[PDB]
Amino acid sequence: MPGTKRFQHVIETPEPGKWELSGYEAAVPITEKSNPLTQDLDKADAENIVRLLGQCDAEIFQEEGQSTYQRLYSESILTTMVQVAGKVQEVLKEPDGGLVVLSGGGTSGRMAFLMSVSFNQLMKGLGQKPLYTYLIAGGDRSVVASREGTEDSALHGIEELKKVAAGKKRVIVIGISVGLSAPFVAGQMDCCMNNTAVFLPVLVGFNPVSMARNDPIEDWSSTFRQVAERMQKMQEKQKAFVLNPAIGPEGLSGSSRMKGGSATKILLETLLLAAHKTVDQGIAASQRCLLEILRTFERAHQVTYSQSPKIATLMKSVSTSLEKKGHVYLVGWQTLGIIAIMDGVECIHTFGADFRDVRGFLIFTFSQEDFLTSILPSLTEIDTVVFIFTLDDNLTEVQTIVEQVKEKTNHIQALAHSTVGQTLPIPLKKLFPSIISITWPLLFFEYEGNFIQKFQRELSTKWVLNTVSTGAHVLLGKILQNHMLDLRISNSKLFWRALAMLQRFSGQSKARCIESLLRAIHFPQPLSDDIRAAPISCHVQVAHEKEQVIPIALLSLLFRCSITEAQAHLAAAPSVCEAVRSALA
Ligand SMILES: C[C@](O)(c1cnc(-c2ccc(S(=O)(=O)c3ccc(N)nc3)s2)c(Cl)c1)C(F)(F)F
Ligand SMILES: O=P(O)(O)OC[C@@H](O)[C@@H](O)[C@H](O)[C@@H](O)CO
Image (cartoon, rainbow, N blue to C red; front, side, top):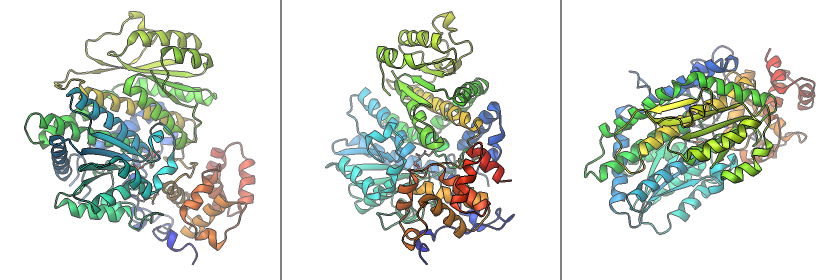
């Protein structure tokens, strides 16, 4: 019938009580699964939330059990890492016409960008000439914006890739998609396999290939699954690579910006650093070299979450300020500035949050006096301002700005990275009563800019920022069990996530859930055969512009009622959350 083929890959809702062993749940990709640790995240105080996410983050480093999925510390994965480091060496040896592209949509793209810069600096430091570049869905503007719709075109992907691979002669394309999902990457990987001479594809994500996305891409004939399967075949001949350890579901279901983003850094920084530091030593990269760095990244989680209690409190002061319709400012220097912006921008799509809700700032890019003149005026009793820096920063610039802000806020906290035995200038630097001091052992670096220290610090910040920003919103009651129900459908992935959530919460059939969703999306227009059969992009374009689409659809299902009737009920209730929560009972 009309719609059949578009919705073919979707599995029927299991019967009440038979979800567990169901065919359905066995095909939910790991990255979209509901994490058992956070079943009750929506009922947790600030300290539990920190504990729970610290724990979910910790799953990145958990080792493989004995009939089960490969993980970061499994020998197949490290062997692949070694192998790829090997292929990066080849390019470094011959840099003329050599290039290394890191590419991804959304947060995978944001992480691509950071890493491209770091390794460019590193070659700058050696006076070698940068070999890295990055690609993000929707162009460079996307690095610091909410642009979730840009990832759905394989041709776009390929076009960006063809622009940058100029007339290069050896190109490594590292396509990063946490879910093995994004059509942007899919096309790139497939294009690379059609020209093995020039290109070498390396696919990075966190699902097994048997769980790689398999629904049709609107502008492309093959699915991610197929592309990934074909890459894995080519890996036997060392002409493609798939790097895909499981790291367990996200604490907030499907919020791949979190564990997904971190594992991407951990994994790629490790590998590329090993490649660099081992070429100049005249020595192959080895499991043992990779391990040193993995274990360092693993210490960094421990180091970071030692500050849990303070972290729980910064959460409360962020949540509070937002509960009162305040704003929250994230002020950081160098790369940690960037990471702050990236965190705040992500709150827009992840939480329906306005750009002012949680905004990042780098000394978006406003200098000392510039920030003092324009932004300083707008602060208020109830706002929260967060400062983020190392002791190797310009701390005269830092202290200055804290000074002005203090008079206007009082809710100011900070996040300070130091090697042990650097001290906080002003013993009255107690403009921060009890800081989040993060103090790093001394490590035997040998490169100029101390790149392992950089990565530790970024990562630790990302965890803190992520845990804080996500935590604040959970406390505000905007999350359901461990799902963001009320999201904005702005790409096809998010459309599938919506549909899945309707099945899960209603317990009703595929067909009913599909019907309720499309009615919610296209109301006031009823379901035509055209509409039922439309490409998913057509539904996205309409949904992207509306509010409460998913809850309206869930209410229509639970009350077995019309869209007209469900909107009226929603408007009859004190809040979306309360309308839904009570409808679930
Ligand atoms: C966990 C849950 O069942 C669920 C959530 N999201 C989903 C999905 C979201 C998006 C998809 S998807 O875009 O088809 C996709 C995305 C990635 C991938 N590798 N394969 C499929 S499935 C599913 Cl299948 C289940 C629940 F409960 F959240 F609804
Ligand atoms: O890395 P993937 O699976 O291709 O996902 C790419 C993007 O959709 C994703 O990173 C999204 O922007 C984030 O808001 C998810 O938390």
